[PDB]
DNA sequence: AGTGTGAG
DNA sequence: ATCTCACACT
């Protein structure tokens, strides 16, 4: 069933207001109440980074000062992420993420895609489950939080699910729609286990590829899951913004919109594959041709040890690193965080990083990074690493006066790679 | 390849 | 993210 890109069952799981839920687990009084998670900033109580769904009803959004949100939601409760060596401390979140990932790994192999989301390949689990119950159909009681995109044509959810279930093939075990339905069953079980063992809620999307799973996950949030079938793709794409498709959120997507004069994914269906290749190249033209028809093949890649570990910090405008002392201090601060993480990495995976990449951005440069250089990473010593990084970046101070740094630095980035 | 692009 | 990480590209 590859010709129609219905060969796999893929799901994407995304935690609802992840940081808020981890905080609600520590301090119970914040549960089922409007609350938020802020990064302490002296001005206005600090910026808000995670908002509960209860608080979103009052118009609360991320990137807005706590006091202004207070005005919008006076009952609003606050949780504050600790700050360390100029950045947020996410140990708590990484550990909760690991908990959930381990729980998901029991049902099918996963691909960790971020701190709060992961792809799941259920093809094998769907086959094995298909043999386990044959002939008896699938009752709606196994899909308490599943939405069937496009149907019908909390009450609506049940009516659409009934219309979906009444038409599912029963005997053809290779039926794409049946495989998706079973995948949604397994995801319902997965999420039930996750809640039971951690108290966390989440959403999921079930379809045939990563792109459709990602779109399906966001259709019915929170604490709900959405199944997007191949037959529902035309309707779903009829008004789906091109820039909302995974990998098309940047320049390529903008280019498609500008060159073809279209806004929705579904409009790409009218162009021929040769036209798309003549305008975007063989590879992107063919990819777009199949993607606008719901076909995509990026495989779900199991456990993978990260290829890099790094951290950085930006110093915009006034904050730009101007003296030599400042650059030395921030390099040391970054290296100390790096050391902490590299140490945990070596403890958990018995591998050591052999290369240190230093990257910096000078004030006034439009590029993301002004330059990058590499040196050996022999010892997990923040002090040593700080001096090595300084040595590769020292040439960049184009000023004979030792009293300052020129041009100033607006970004410092340290990264450990070449693991072995 | 080191840079640029993009997902989260 | 008003950061972490992956990887495509002669
Ligand atoms: C996108 C984003 C996320 N985060 C953090 C906090 C979030 O809890 C975590 C996951 O990010 P998101 O998944 O983007 O958002 P969310 O989990 O808070 O809520 P929902 O999925 O229901 O929309 O990463 C930021 O601090 N700044 C950001 O810009
Ligand atoms: Ca989330
Ligand atoms: Ni020293």
Image (cartoon, coloured by chain):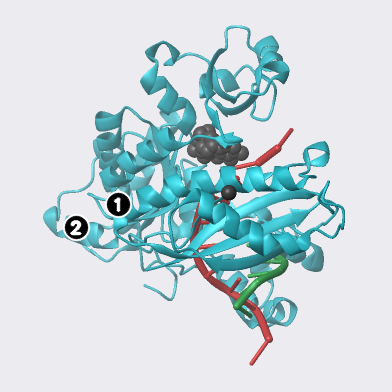
Chain colours: A cyan, B green, C red
Element type where label 2 sits in the image: helix
Given the image, what chain letter belongs to the residue carrying mark 1?
A
Asked whether the residues under marks 2 and 1 belong to the same chain, the reply is yes
Q: Is residue A245 above or below residue A16?
A: below
Q: Which quadrant of the figure has residue A58?
A: top right
Mark 1 CB in 8 Å range of ligand 1?
no
Kindly identify which residue carries mark 1.
A348
Residue A352, percent from left and from top:
38, 62
Q: Is residue A113 above or below residue A256?
A: above
Name the residue located 23 percent from the left edge and 57 percent from the top edge: A125
Residue A18, percent from left and from top:
46, 33
Q: Residues within 10 Å of mark 2 (few under 14, many from 20)?
A: some
Name the residue located 37 percent from the left edge and 33 percent from the top edge: A158
Kindly identify which residue carries mark 2.
A130
**Residue A83 in the figure: left or right of residue A340:** right
Name the residue located 30 percent from the left edge and 57 percent from the top edge: A349
């Amino acid at each position: 069933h590859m010709a129609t890109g219905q060969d796999r069952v893929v799901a994407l799981v995304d935690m609802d207001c992840f940081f808020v839920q981890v905080e609600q687990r520590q301090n119970p009084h914040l549960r089922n109440k409007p609350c938020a998670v802020v990064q302490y900033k002296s001005w206005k109580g600090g910026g808000i980074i995670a908002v509960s769904y209860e608080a979103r009803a009052f118009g609360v959004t991320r990137s807005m000062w706590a006091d202004d949100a207070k005005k919008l939601c006076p009952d609003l409760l606050l949780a504050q992420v600790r700050e360390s060596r100029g950045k947020a401390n996410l140990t708590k979140y990484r550990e909760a993420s690991v908990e959930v990932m381990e729980i998901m790994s029991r049902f099918a192999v996963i691909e960790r895609a971020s701190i709060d989301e992961a792809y799941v390949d259920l093809t094998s689990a769907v086959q094995e489950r298909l043999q386990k119950l044959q002939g008896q159909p699938i009752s709606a009681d196994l899909l308490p939080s599943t939405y069937i995109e496009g149907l019908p044509q909390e009450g609506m959810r049940k009516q659409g699910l009934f219309q979906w279930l009444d038409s599912l093939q029963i005997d053809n075990l290779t039926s794409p729609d049946l495989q998706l339905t079973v995948g949604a069953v397994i995801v319902e079980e997965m999420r039930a286990a996750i809640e039971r063992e951690t108290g966390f809620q989440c959403s999921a999307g079930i379809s045939h590829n990563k792109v459709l799973a990602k779109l399906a996950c966001g259709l019915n949030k929170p604490n709900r899951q959405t199944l997007v079938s191949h037959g529902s793709v035309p309707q779903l794409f009829s008004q789906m913004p091109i820039r909302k498709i995974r990998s098309l959120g940047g320049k390529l997507g903008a280019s498609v919109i500008e060159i073809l004069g279209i806004e929705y994914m579904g409009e790409l269906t009218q162009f021929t594959e040769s036209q798309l290749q003549s305008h975007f190249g063989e590879k992107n033209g063919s990819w777009l041709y199949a993607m606008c028809r719901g076909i995509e093949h990026d495989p779900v890649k199991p456990r993978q040890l990260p290829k890099t570990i790094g951290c950085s910090k930006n110093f915009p405008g006034k904050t730009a690193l101007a003296t030599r002392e400042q650059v030395q201090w921030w390099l040391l601060q970054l290296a100390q965080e790096l050391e902490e993480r590299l140490t945990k990495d070596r403890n958990d995976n018995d591998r050591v990083a052999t290369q240190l990449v230093v990257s910096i951005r000078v004030q006034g440069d439009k590029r993301l990074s002004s330059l990058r250089r590499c040196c050996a990473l022999t010892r997990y010593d923040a002090h040593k690493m700080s001096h090595d990084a300084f040595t590769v970046i020292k040439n960049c101070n184009t000023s004979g006066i030792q009293t300052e740094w020129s041009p100033p630095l607006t970004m410092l980035f340290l990264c450990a790679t070449k693991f072995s």
